[PDB]
Image (cartoon, rainbow, N blue to C red; front, side):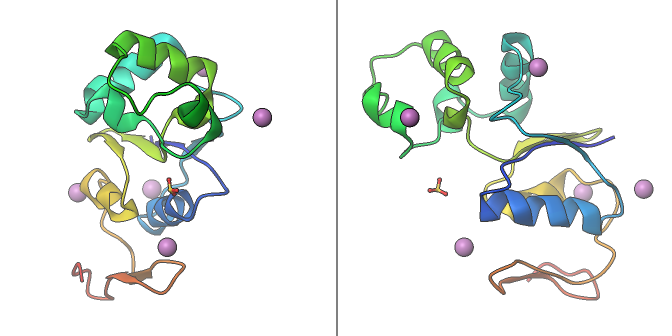
Length: 138
Ligand SMILES: O=S([O-])[O-]
Ligand SMILES: [Cs+]
Ligand SMILES: [Cs+]
Ligand SMILES: [Cs+]
Ligand SMILES: [Cs+]
Ligand SMILES: [Cs+]
């Protein structure tokens, strides 16, 4: 029972999805840009991730730039409401498994919450090796 909030256009999100598959399960895939979490779900994701609301904000996207969000003049709830009204602000990928929830940046963070071991060596799509055939992290 795994869920990934996935952006097919992001290498980090692609590598995370293939690592999930390499542990042997096909996750439920939520294209969050199109189908963002509800307010309640997003608050829960953030609490489970143990990160600040602002640490979930993606920089360098049009609403972050034009809404001035680099500056420290927003409460946590104002930032959650911006994220819901402009879903590209939600950084990615978020992964939920029975063991917990993480913002998988970098992608190998997901190894923390996958229940089953990678089934073989895993190399990221730019050739960065992540785990060898024996299962050791490199
Ligand atoms: O992938 S970075 O530009 O958020
Ligand atoms: Cs499985
Ligand atoms: Cs939803
Ligand atoms: Cs636009
Ligand atoms: Cs684990
Ligand atoms: Cs890269």
